[PDB]
Image: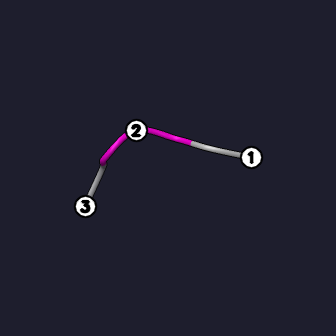
Amino acid sequence: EVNPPVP
């Protein structure tokens, strides 16, 4: 899967 930048 792939997700947005959420550090």
How busy is the neighbourhood of tag 3: few (under 14 within 10 Å), some, or many (20 plus)? few
Give the magenta-colored segment's residue range. Answer: 3-5
Q: Residue at x 30, y 49 (%)?
A: 6
Residue 2 spot, x, y in % from top left: 62, 44
Residue 1 spot, x, y in % from top left: 74, 46
- Please tell me whether mark 2 sits on a helix, a strand or a loop: loop
- The residue most toward the front is 2
Figure quadrant of residue 4:
top left
Q: Tell me the residue that label 3 is attached to.
A: 7
Q: Which mark is residue 4?
A: 2
- The residue most toward the bottom is 7
Q: What's the amino acid at mark 1?
A: Glu
Horizontal relation, residue 1 to residue 5: left or right = right
Which one is in front in this view, the residue at disc 3 or the one at disc 2?
2
Residue 7 spot, x, y in % from top left: 25, 61
> Is most of the magenta stretch helix, strand or loop?
loop
Q: Tell me the residue that label 1 is attached to.
A: 1
- Please tell me whether mark 3 sits on a helix, a strand or a loop: loop
Q: Earlier in the sequence, mark 3 or mark 1?
A: 1
Q: CA distance from mark 3 to mark 2?
A: 9 Å
Q: CA distance from mark 3 to mark 1?
A: 17 Å
Residue 3 spot, x, y in % from top left: 52, 41
